[PDB]
Length: 301
Length: 10
Image 1 (cartoon, rainbow over the protein chains, first blue to last red):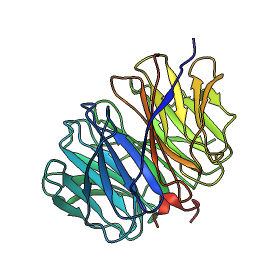
Image 2 (cartoon, one colour):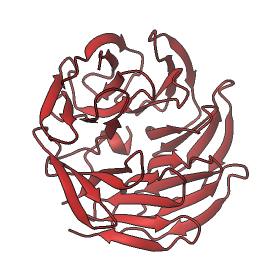
Image 3 (tube, chains in turn purple, green):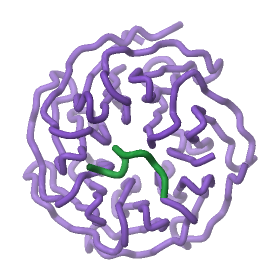
C-alpha cells in the first residue's frame, strides 16, 4: 500500500519565508506562521484565506494550537511568545522572559501550560491563564530546536543543536532521560507517547524507544543539513512518517518498513514545515524565501 | 526574518 497525495491548493500571501504550519485539533483550520511577522488562518478543506493575526515585532518561528482549537501560541525572534484568541485575533498574553529568539512552542493537552524553547538554551513552562513563567529549565548547552508534550502532558521532550534529546517530568522539572548518542533539529512524541521521532542535521530521522534508549527505525533519502524541519506521524490512513526536505520535496516513508512511499514535488524552496490533518488524509507543506507558499495535498489512503 | 527560516547554529 502507498499513498497518492495530490496537490489541491497553493496558498499565497505571506511576504517572507513561511516557518510553520499546524492544523487545528478540530480539523477546521490551518495556521501558518512566517518570517513576515504574521500568522495566517486558512480553511483546511477549501484552502480559503480566513484571517491575518499580527502584533509580533519580529518574525515568527513557530505556532501551535490549544487542544480546544480556540487559542494559538506563537514564538518570535522578538524574544516573546504571544497567546492569541483565534476567533477575534486579539493578543491575550505576551510571554516575556526568554533572553533570545523563541524558536519552538506547544500547548499541553490540558492546555493550561505552554512549553517553549529558545536560542537562550532554556526551556520555559508558562501558565496560560496568567501568562507567567512557571519554570525555567536549563535544558541544553545550545539553541533548543523543539519542545513537545506527551499525550497526557506529564512529560516534555526537548532537542537542541547541542546534540541531545531530553525527557523532562513536567511537574517537577527534572530531567528523566537523556538520549545521548549531530545537531538535533526536531523531536516529538509519537501519538501513543511511547516513542520519539528525532531529526538530526545529518539527513536522518530516527524513531526511538526512549525508555529503552534504543533506536527502532531510521528514515533517510531526504536532505536535512541546515534547517529545523518539522516531521510528523501520519495516522489517518496508512501509518506514515512525513517530513520536509532541503531539496524542495515532501518525503513520505512507511513507518514500519522505512521505505520511501512518496515524494511530493512542486515547492520551489526548502520545505521547512509539514503537518498532517487529524481526521482526513491531508498534508500541509510550507517553504522558505524563494517560495513563500503553503500547499495542501490529499490522498485516498 | 525568523530563526527557523535561517540556518540553525548558535
